[PDB]
Length: 271
Ligand SMILES: O[C@@H]1[C@H](O)[C@H](O)CO[C@H]1O
Image 1 (cartoon, helix red, strand yellow):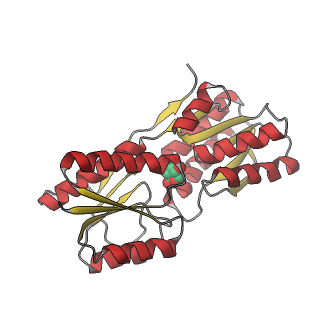
Image 2: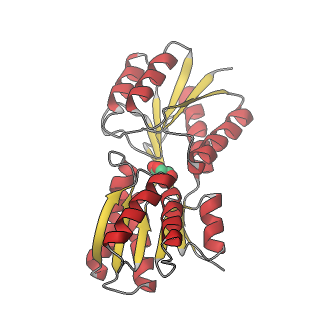
């Protein structure tokens, strides 16, 4: 059994657990051995993970960068060891990558901003909780969101990173609420931060604020159905992991693949 390795940015996020299960289920199906390594949002740890795999008989490296610019060293190391690299969910700015599989994050941010304008109205006062700064996902969602801003003349009271983390998303929202109690809507770049923000508005008695997340995880989807979360942009993590293993199979077979494989997004609301 050829071994395929999956280096995921973190496992302390439901989105990445689903991504891992999708890859795992497809690996079982195609008869591969899947090794899963966790970088814990640490580029130094990612590098150590990749260096350890290049001598384990790893045939293909599926990688979710902790940082789109910093991952280039790990990619170049996989290149040196003649191990083809496929990026999942986030890009590698440089380094030789056979294929990239991800959602259209620029579209995702605009759609998020457009839904806010539809509910909170044009010229609405918003706060944006951003993801991990150096990743392509956060960067692109912000750009897409900046398009809805200009178009809907939104007044952005504040925009700040909460690192795709639920607890950080809670503390950052907590701190911003004290300074900006007039907030009407919040765009949270993932469901974890969106759920943290919700808890902050809860602790503050500020139930009037409209929160839009991203991912459509089990928790994110439930909060929308319970009426707490206004909407989330559903991604298909399991299919990104599966498509990644599927593509790793073709490369090993000698079949050429596309340099990019998009995955569908879907606005999620109650009913
Ligand atoms: O797309 C992924 C998911 O949104 C995850 O929740 C955080 O990292 C992003 O890159």
